[PDB]
Image (tube, rainbow over all chains, first blue to last red; front, side):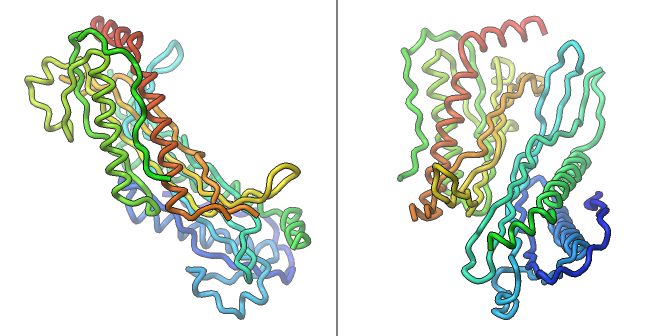
Length: 186
Length: 187
């Protein structure tokens, strides 16, 4: 399990804009172990915090849009809420052709949405989606049939790629150019 | 809008072609936003309709709820075991900013994916997998104020049910099954 994406920005200086970061709510389907869901949500929660601190923002963590005191509301630039799901489907066959061997795979479906919310009216001003589907892991190949991994290990291969891609897409959307534009439109 | 898990199987009944297919009850997971009864009724409709489609196409159809309930007598005689797994999830409260032509709108939107497995009955070997992507189905809930969530869920699910039945019915054509029959013959 590698729910870590390294952050390579420089330490930017305090820009005095404060962002509210809500714990992401990512549903999973039954074949994914519960501990992975919490690992995944806990990693995105802290890693986006670091990343936002690293870019000059200060961060109020909450775990629900309920908590949020009218205090923090009156001050914060925006709230960042992530919701969605990841599911894993098992035992899909891809048949052989001239170049490729026949394979049994696991494969994801699912989607993650990140809302940009104004703290007072609670209006969503913008939504950014990451598609996390069609990430594949090979469990058997036919060369003699050969087992490559067990199921749990496919689940893991797939969650890591998914985590990664999410963190890559999100960190890229939250650039300075985008954020400063956000501020002005508001 | 009311639930509508029914696709009209239009077509002449076909001379009984003598092949038997085993149909297993579809396993379709759902996310928290969708009532369990919708899942059940979505799984039940696909099951009966696929039996009706098959029969109307000349096959004998044997129904079971799990592959383990298939008796040897059946395994020995069946052409094919069809076996559907997947999920459908609905995401709520996605905004689509306005532009020159369209008002700003808030929507609900699906994700998920269905997989139909084609299985050789004796060995239990999967021979072929056919997928239907059911993601990116949208319902508008608010314009800058159309509906609420449960009504949008109903619409999205109907559109997903329609898409599954159309893709599978076209996948399980006479040309494809005869081809599949020939392919096992050699195998």
